[PDB]
Amino acid sequence: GLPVCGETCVGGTCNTPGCTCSWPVCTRN
Image 1 (tube, rainbow, N blue to C red):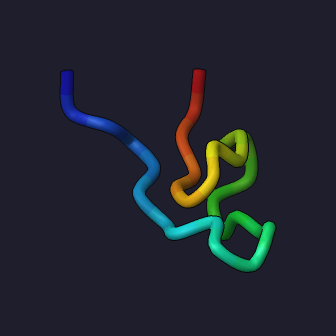
Image 2: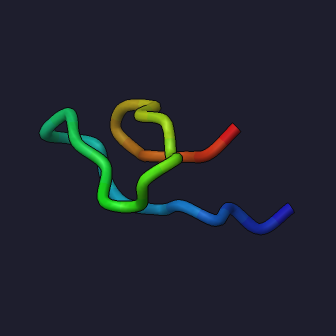
Image 3: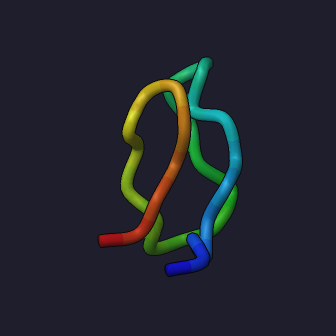
């Protein structure tokens, strides 16, 4: 499955609201 989110949560942050941080990458469950 193609991940909706893909922002690096290296700095403990996510751009897309709704995406959970899964260091070092944000992803939505």
